[PDB]
Amino acid sequence: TEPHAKKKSKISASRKLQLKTLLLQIAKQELEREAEERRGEKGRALSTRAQPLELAGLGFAELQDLARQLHARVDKVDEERYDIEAKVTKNITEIADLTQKIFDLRGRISADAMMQALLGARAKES
Amino acid sequence: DDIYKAAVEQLTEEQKNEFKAAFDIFVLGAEDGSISTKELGKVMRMLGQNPTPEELQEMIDEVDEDGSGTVDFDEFLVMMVRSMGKSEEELSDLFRMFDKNADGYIDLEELKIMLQATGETITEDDIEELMKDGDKNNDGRIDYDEFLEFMKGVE
Amino acid sequence: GKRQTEREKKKKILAERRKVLAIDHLNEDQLREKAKELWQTIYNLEAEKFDLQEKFKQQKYEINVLRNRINDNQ
Ligand SMILES: [Ca+2]
Ligand SMILES: [Ca+2]
Ligand SMILES: [Ca+2]
């Protein structure tokens, strides 16, 4: 290979660093915003999927039947939860495998001490 | 690179003058006024170190910006500051926030949107240079691995 | 093959998690509380289901990125 020009930039590395720092800050704010919005979404989903009990005016036998109905629903919802959990579990196995794959594909003396040795008393600032 | 370059920009003149005096010791007698593995080895051994030729070559390659196989004074300053950030999991979550269309890449539009959201005055040069800084393989976008290098050492 | 083992495992885990409903000694007031308790269980299970659905979506994103990284680095 032959030599080539160095990368040159219109802006200072000091400016780039400031911009990157601010970029990470706002990404972090957007992450908190996402979490808050997801909490809101969770509240609304739970309003629909698990609506409040109406117990007023149910007699003894009606209450016995309701408890049996709710207990049956517990079984059904647990089964649905299990099914999504099973998909999450399979994704974990896939994530672990792909993470290993990409890792594989991707696979002194300090200036202080050096300056003291080379320059002796002429090293002050450094 | 970026965090080291910034440290170099902030060196005082007297600091740079002292580094120049050190650089002159390294390059004494060199054909092209530059530090090759020959000069680097000589000085490292003078300093009591015993690097292999491979370690020597690697030390040069780390800071060589023009592929000369040698270290000039500007590259020497970077070598000096190098000789003295967030976790990957944390950066992975932040990456997702840049990636607004969820395609696994940060494009120029997504970078622009993020930069404007900072509240700083964003010039066209700010946008073009950051993208060029981040995009190592010249496809005009920042992939996950490029993003990690791009943010390396950023607080 | 793999399907009948996944199915029997599912049946086994759900069986182990199931509670006995014993309400036959309870009066009206106790039954109302028992109903509220079961409702809360359903609520908590739905909440856990929601968390898993959100995790699943983030996982699909992560998998897509990983697949792109692998393709680009081969
Ligand atoms: Ca060079
Ligand atoms: Ca994108
Ligand atoms: Ca790129």
Image (cartoon, grey):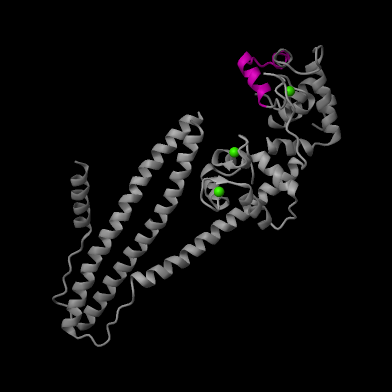
Which image quarter has ligand 3? top right
Q: In the image as oriented, which residue stretches furthest toward the front?
A: B139
Q: Report the label total.
A: 0
Q: Residue at x 36, y 72 (%)?
A: A48
**Front residue of A125 and B40:** B40
* Image quarter of the C terminus of chain A: top right
State the image coordinates of residue B75 (x, y, percent, origin top left).
75, 27
Splitting the image into 4 quarters, where does residue A30 fall?
bottom right
Vertical comparison of B62 with A51: above or below: above
State the image coordinates of residue A107 (x, y, percent, origin top left).
50, 28
Q: Residue at x 61, y 51 (%)?
A: B110
Q: Is residue B39 left or right of residue A64?
A: right
State the image coordinates of residue A54 (x, y, percent, origin top left).
29, 82
Q: Is residue A81 visible?
A: yes
Q: Is residue A93 left or right of residue B6?
A: left
Q: In the image as oriented, which residue stretches furthest toward the left?
A: C24
**Front residue of A50 and B47:** A50
Q: Is residue C10 left or right of residue A37?
A: left
Splitting the image into 4 quarters, where does residue B7 fall?
top right
Vertical comparison of C65 with A28: above or below: above
State the image coordinates of residue C5 (x, y, percent, origin top left).
19, 45
Q: In the image as oriented, which residue stretches furthest toward the bottom?
A: A57
* Image quarter of the N terminus of chain A: top right
Query: Is residue B49 within the magenta segment?
Result: yes
**What range is drawn magenta here?**
B42-62
Q: Residue at x 81, y 17 (%)?
A: B33
Query: Is residue B4 within the magenta segment?
Result: no
Vertical comparison of B25 with C71: above or below: above
User: Does the magenta stretch mainly form a helix, a strand or a loop?
Assistant: helix
Q: Is residue B84 visible?
A: no
